[PDB]
Length: 243
Ligand code: NA
Image: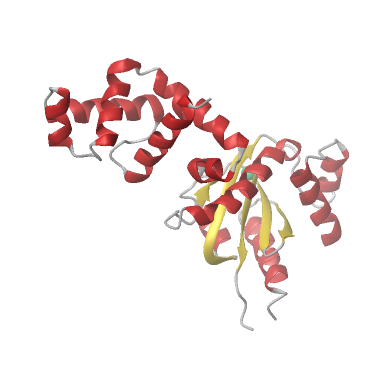
């Protein structure tokens, strides 16, 4: 196992140095170069004492866990974080990922988008790293959390790609809803989710307001009645107006 070479492959994805030769470097480490690539970042699990080799233990676990599930992983460190690239399609509820999480501390883990192949994974890396930089700003984040689920936090920290993603992935689909839905959303967010009250203000049954929020969820995938969703819609609508 050549772990200088493993780190150089990870670091070349992190830096966006993704020429063809990256693939042979990876094949050489038993990466299937056709597979999807997902970057995640977290802290290594704290070991029984020893404590600089936490990172080396956690790397080994990660690679073992991958092998056991039929996948490959490459790792590198990013100061006190461990950066892992893992192969294959990746579901939130699936067992590979539950096991993988045991290699990390009981502290945030941020999962980047899945890329089609290793050489396409620079954005996955940049977003997972940006999310990890941003995750302190949502203390209640779930473990794990998607980079794309931290757009307010990344936006407030100055990550341009988060601002763009609020437009492209929240505002643009919102905008498909037309003025009756956006107006209802805006009112509901200002009443703080107080349905009876808002309904009176919008001259409609409570159940019409509820139905219209369920439509907001149809256009955008965010549920205005869930406090996280509602916060993301509200920040996204702001950013929408100021660009
Ligand atoms: Na993957």
